[PDB]
């Protein structure tokens, strides 16, 4: 829209991070103030500052903001584990005759001991062939959310149909687990000799081969 | 309750009102000249 | 005070939707009540606000007159009505409360926000889910542990709550989310870790409970005998 | 800039009747009119405001409906308690109020007859040097009463002031009296003094004429 | 739950300064729109001046000059000062508070009389009935308003019609009072009308008898 925000920003536990929210002269460059909203992943957003100098009740003193010309600056004293949320700047627009919000920024402060991915393949059972469908699963666990590319091969040509990627879910030990599904038919299931699922992560490739017969 | 009213009152823009009560669109041009260099100034003629 | 909304709503591409944003612990007083939406992967937009002493709503120029927002002073609740549903409008809709002040800025700030309403559009109708057993092979159980579970297929209204032995198992249980497909179908996964010594004396069953379809299917699993 | 004219001034209605008082303004005003009820000797009070809604303490018998030019205060049931004057007021952008004339509602009464009672000045007023002669009107209805005096078979104008009493609470009877002020020099010049009246209750006008020093 | 009282009314010369005092019990003097509506005797109401919650005031076309409004927050009272007065300024006014475009609250009124005359004793002249009948006495050349009358020291209360005061061209009011009396009781009972008022403190008891000539 008319409001421009950085896509993502990295932080460290102890340093200071400055976020700049700039917009058009009709909304930001005019006399209208800015308002910051923190949207937690799973919680409704709440007001952070209002009037560019005041702080509502319940807002910690580490959060501060200021206005300088046609730009808005957000200063946070330190970064905690609960600061991983999207921040938006809201201001009144004269041309659009309504309040507008910023594009948003992502502040991620996290770190995990990423290791070599482990892949397990489960061929479909005999009872799945009577449903006129074939579903091939490629279970992967103990990996990192980055580099989750999934490839399928039939030892003669790569498969470019039915491939998809699922987002991972956080476990109880700071781990992410995901999988991938491949829809096929029992008519061509017996034609191919073997099937494999290829997962590439940080240059480490693990290949597993399952034999239907 | 009593002695408790909203400060905003609505405008009655009926078409049967008088000339002085007609809805007029008003635009205010506010000019401010500071010591900063000017960015918008007078236009340029395009005579034959 | 707090603002309470309704639950998740599933509609059709071209139907009409309506919810309520009730207030608990107090009425709307004289402050404006506004609605602000947010979407995954996108920013936040604005549609208008409702004054609870006069019933006048000011819309936004980005949206046409296909949406109406109304409120009543008797119940102190805000209602909205949007027509001509589209697959783009798959975002959650929040109700917000404005707090004005005096100054040179005069920018409206949202101090209080609603709990949240989930709105999703899908052309597919309600069908009956099918569950099929999964069991490792002989080569998978190289060590003393085996990984097995149950998979749910062709379910239209969202992944369901998966419980092992009616909630008797709490260690080693993991939940996997769904994913968009070519036909809009959703598929989940559920894998647990069990010792190999318990495969001959204790059986595993999956209890699926589906509120909108009023169905409950009980199925058993067992390791394969051929391999 | 704006002037206020009201079509009704004095109307008479029974208990089961609508007074139908109409309010007209020079320029069109949209639903920004309020009505009042001021009793004689009592401070006024508001009845309706914005010509659409109703005050909490005011009984709901009063009603009004006017969009831009024509306003009304029709009452479904007329009560003896709300017998007072009515005004419609409209303000300006600088809160400039504009109040108009009063419309009074009176109870209907028999026409009856204007009994004329002449009263020559007494001999005590001769020493004062001022001569005042009056003629009395009683049990007359309605207010359309001619009070013109005839002296020496000639028309007299600009010499009498009317005095109208208020309606009594017993039977609503009207009384009229006019006082004429003249010098003692002009009193002896004229010989015939009389006043004539005209009403719906008389087929012919009734005039009582006396003379100076007539016993 | 509103209550407004006014004070300061009375008789004063045209060439003088008069200060009014309007008090509000349950209302503040700096948080509402107030109107000074003045109604002439025998005529309808008329707007005179308006004051806002802030330091602003407005006046009508006829009373644009010679008017000053100064509220007082110390005692919660409203003050209106009239530095110059005219002969048409005599009326009854009511201080009040109200909202925009209309006002609902109302208060009492104080009568003000302005003239070049002073207190004058009332002259009572009998009215000889002609030979039912009507009898009474005429009050002429008296000032100021009001004057009460009584028949037989209040014994007679039937048929009493007290006409209101009328202003003459000489600046003095006139009053007439009549009663209904049967002709059979003219020669039996004696009727005396009492005319008195506070500003002059005069008590004259004059009887009316239908005798003599002219």
Image: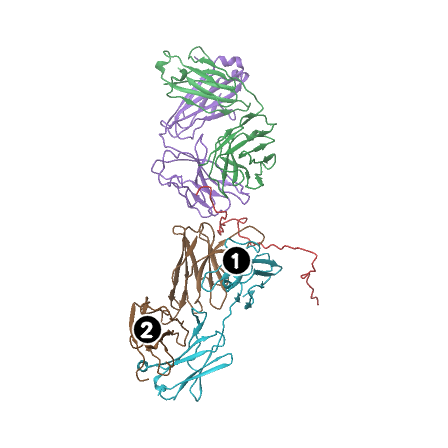
Chain colours: A cyan, B red, C brown, D purple, E green
Residue at mark 2: chain: C
Looking at the picture, tell me which residue is in the foreground, E171 or A144.
Answer: A144
Q: Position of residue D116 (x, y in %)?
A: 41, 22
Q: Is residue E37 above or below residue E14?
A: below
Determine the secondary structure under disc 1: strand
Number of numbered callouts drawn: 2
* Residue D135 placement, left or right of A89: left
Alpha carbon distance from label 2 to label 1:
44 Å
Q: Position of residue B3 (x, y in %)?
A: 47, 41
- At horizontal 29% and vertical 72% (from top left) the residue drawn is C218
**Quadrant (top left, top right, bottom left, bottom right) of the N terminus of chain E:** top left
Determine the secondary structure under disc 2: loop
Number of the label disc, if any, that sits on residue C206:
none
Looking at the picture, tell me which residue is in the foreground, D69 or A75.
Answer: A75
- What residue is pinned by disc 2? C129
Q: Is residue E13 above or below residue C45?
A: above
* Residue A128 placement, left or right of D26: left
Q: Position of residue D11 (x, y in %)?
A: 40, 36
Q: Are marks 2 and 1 in contact (CB under 8 Å)?
A: no
Q: Position of residue E133 (x, y in %)?
A: 38, 18
Residue at mark 1: chain: A
- What residue is pinned by disc 1? A48
Q: Is residue A86 above or below residue A61?
A: below
Neighbor class of circle 1 (other Cα within 10 Å; few <14, some 14-19, many 20+) is many
Residue C153 seen from this side: no
Looking at the picture, tell me which residue is in the foreground, D125 or E46.
Answer: E46
Looking at the picture, tell me which residue is in the foreground, A66 or C50.
Answer: A66
Instruction: Name the residue at the top extreme.
Output: E212
* Front of the two marks 2 and 1: 1
């Amino acid at each position: 829209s008319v409001l421009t925000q950085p896509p993502s920003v990295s932080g460290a536990p102890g340093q200071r991070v400055t976020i700049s929210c700039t917009g058009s002269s009709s909304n930001i460059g005019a006399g209208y103030d800015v308002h910051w909203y923190q949207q937690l992943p799973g919680t409704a957003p709440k007001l952070l500052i209002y009037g560019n100098s005041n702080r509502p009740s319940g807002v910690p003193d580490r959060f501060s903001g200021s206005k300088s010309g046609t730009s808005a600056s957000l200063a946070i004293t330190g970064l905690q584990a609960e600061d991983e949320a999207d921040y938006y700047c809201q201001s009144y627009d004269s041309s659009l005759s309504g309040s507008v919000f910023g594009g948003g920024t992502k502040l991620t402060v996290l770190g995990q001991p990423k290791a070599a991915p482990s892949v397990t393949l489960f061929p479909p059972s005999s009872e799945e062939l009577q449903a006129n469908k074939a579903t091939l699963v490629c279970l992967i666990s103990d990996f990192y959310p980055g580099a989750v590319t999934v490839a399928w091969k039939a030892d003669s040509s790569p498969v470019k149909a039915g491939v998809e990627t699922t987002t991972p879910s956080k476990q109880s030990n700071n781990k992410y687990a995901a999988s991938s599904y491949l829809s096929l038919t029992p008519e061509q299931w017996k034609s191919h000799r073997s099937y494999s699922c290829q997962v590439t992560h940080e240059g480490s490739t693990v290949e597993k081969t399952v034999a239907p017969t | 309750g009593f002695n408790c009213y909203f400060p905003l009152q609505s405008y009655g823009f009926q078409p049967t009102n008088g000339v002085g009560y007609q809805p007029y669109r008003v635009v205010v041009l506010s000019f401010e000249l500071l010591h900063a260099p000017a960015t918008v100034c007078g236009p340029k003629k395009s005579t034959n | 005070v707090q603002l309470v909304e309704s639950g998740a709503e599933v509609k059709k591409p071209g139907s009409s939707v309506k919810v309520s944003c009730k207030a608990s612990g107090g009425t709307f007083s004289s402050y404006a009540i506004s609605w602000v939406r947010q979407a995954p992967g996108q920013g936040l937009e604005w549609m208008g606000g409702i004054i609870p002493i006069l019933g006048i709503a000011n819309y936004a120029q980005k949206f046409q007159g296909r949406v109406t927002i109304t409120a009543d002073k008797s119940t102190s609740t805000a209602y909205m009505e949007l027509s001509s549903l589209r697959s783009e409008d798959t975002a959650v809709y929040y109700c917000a409360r404005e707090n004005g002040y005096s100054g040179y800025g005069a920018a409206a700030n949202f101090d209080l926000w609603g709990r949240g309403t989930l709105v999703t559009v899908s052309s597919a109708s309600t069908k009956g889910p099918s569950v099929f057993p999964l069991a490792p092979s002989s080569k998978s159980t190289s060590g003393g542990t085996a990984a097995l579970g149950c998979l749910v297929k062709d379910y239209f209204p969202e992944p369901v709550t998966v419980s092992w032995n009616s909630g008797a198992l709490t260690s080693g249980v993991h939940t996997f989310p769904a994913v968009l497909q070519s036909s809009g179908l959703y598929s989940l996964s559920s894998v647990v870790t069990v010792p190999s010594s318990s495969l001959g004396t204790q059986t595993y069953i999956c209890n699926v409970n589906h509120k909108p379809s009023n169905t409950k299917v009980d199925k058993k699993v067992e390791p394969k005998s051929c391999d | 800039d704006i002037q206020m004219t009201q079509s009704p001034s004095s109307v008479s209605a029974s208990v089961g009747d609508r007074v139908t008082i109409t309010c007209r303004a020079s320029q069109g005003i949209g639903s920004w009119l309020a009505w009042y009820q001021q009793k004689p000797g009592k401070a006024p009070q508001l009845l309706i405001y914005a010509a659409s809604t109703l005050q909490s303490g005011v009984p709901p018998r009063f009603s009004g409906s006017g969009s831009g030019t024509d306003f009304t205060l029709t009452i479904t049931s007329l009560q003896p308690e709300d017998f007072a004057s009515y005004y419609c007021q409209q303000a300006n952008s600088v809160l400039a109020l504009t109040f108009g004339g009063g419309t009074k509602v009176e109870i209907k009464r028999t026409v009856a007859a204007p009994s004329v009672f002449i009263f020559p000045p007494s001999d005590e007023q001769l020493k004062s040097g001022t001569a005042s002669v009056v003629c009395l009107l009683n049990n007359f209805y309605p207010r359309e009463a001619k009070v013109q005096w005839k002296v020496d078979n000639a028309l007299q104008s600009g010499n009498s002031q009317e005095s109208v009493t208020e309606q009594d609470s017993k039977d609503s009877t009207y009384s009229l009296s006019s006082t004429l002020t003249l010098s003692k020099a002009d009193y002896e010049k004229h010989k015939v003094y009389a006043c004539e009246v005209t009403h719906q209750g008389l087929s012919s006008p009734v005039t009582k004429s006396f003379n100076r020093g007539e016993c």
